[PDB]
Length: 17
RNA sequence: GGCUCGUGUAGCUCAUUAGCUCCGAGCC
Image (cartoon, rainbow, N blue to C red; front, side):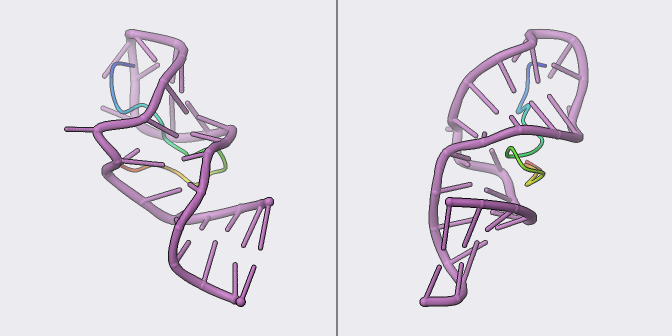
């Protein structure tokens, strides 16, 4: 919720803050 | 193009930290 909230960049590219 | 990769104080679900989109190194 209220946070970076992203995970992947749209193709399993992930986000890892 | 296209994929992987990756916080980019880049968006949506804003409670939920992952799942989709953006695009740079790489080949060219």
